[PDB]
Image: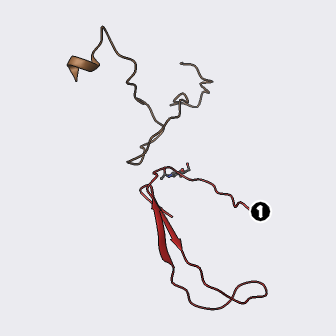
Amino acid sequence: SNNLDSKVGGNYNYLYRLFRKSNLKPFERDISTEIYQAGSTPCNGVEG
Amino acid sequence: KNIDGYFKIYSKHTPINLVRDLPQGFSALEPLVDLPIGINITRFQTLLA
Ligand SMILES: *[C@@H]1O[C@H](CO)[C@@H](O)[C@H](O)[C@H]1NC(C)=O
């Protein structure tokens, strides 16, 4: 699709979930936008 | 029930004569329809008239 999906420097219409608290079962769609917390410190919707 | 997102609907209707609680008798349900929706159902509610 490089002749199509590639536009200028990037296309943000196609996104993905990079982080998840565990391994998700197959054939599942996760729309949760919650910030991934790897520690015990509360993220509160911001990076840190 | 569900299998990998396949909702299994098994419907059986038989006439009975009952006061309260449950009658004692054997029943084998039959499939009605199939709804391969593929969504997670964590809760349900019964609708009444
Ligand atoms: C449905 O959600 C429950 C509670 O989060 C989870 O335990 C279960 O694995 C989920 N099932 C499916 C089919 O996604």
As rendered, which of A47 and B48 lies closer to the eye? B48
Who's the residue at 59% across and 53% down the image?
Answer: B42
Q: Nearer the viewer, residue B31 or B41?
A: B31
- Image coordinates for residue A38, horizontal then vertical, percent: 50, 31
Ligand 1 within 8 angstroms of badge 1 C-beta: no
Q: Residue at x 27, y 16 (%)?
A: A6
Q: Nearer the viewer, residue A12 or B48?
A: B48
Quadrant into which the N terminus of chain A falls: top left
Residue B5: x and y in percent read 44, 55
Question: Which chain's colour is brown?
Answer: A
Classify A30 as above or below B33: above
Q: Say left or right for B25 vs A21.
A: right
Q: Which residue is mark 1?
A: B49
Q: Colour of chain B?
A: red
Label 1 SS: loop
Chain under callout 1: B
A7 vs B11: above or below = above
Q: Position of residue B20 (x, y in %)?
A: 78, 84
- Give the x, y percent position of residue B32: 49, 70
Q: Residue at x 60, y 27 (%)?
A: A41
